[PDB]
Image (cartoon, rainbow, N blue to C red; front, side):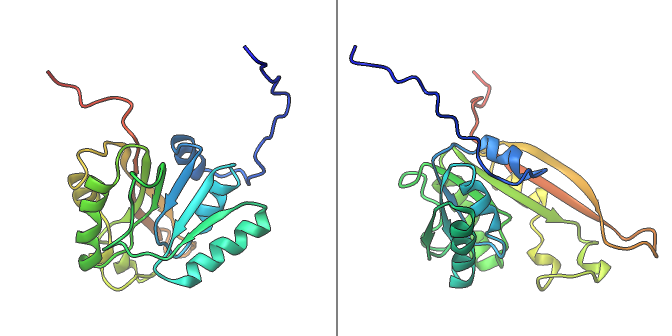
Length: 202
């Protein structure tokens, strides 16, 4: 036996302490992590400051350049992919790990994406979905276009019986007010993870 190095050199990862996003990061493998297109790819650079090699996709250069900007500013590396969720999205054969921050897609790209997370995502990527209630866009607080673009547990969990979810529950969050005393939000959260437990049967 040649020699074994005494690993005295620690490196605690300089990352801002976060509530939700650190649990999913604890689930994600510390290797090559594929992020999908999202209006806030800020989460990608967070995962990179964890010492992880993060490769981010966005169909727009505005998301990629912003993720890559925060990378250099945080002293970390992204791999910038300009790809499309109907053609090249998530390939767990080419990549090692995956993170998919809540999929905002119309029925066209949406019904393209769910078969890609079923077949294309092999175990070792996490699907992070924060959906909204049909009462949410009706609050007139905001909306992408229509309550159609709200990804709900009914749809998401049904399309992924392979990707069993660590989190599948309705979580309430208060909206910024103190007048109506009922300016709250009915939300739902999903964390898909690689099953260390196989589907239990005989």
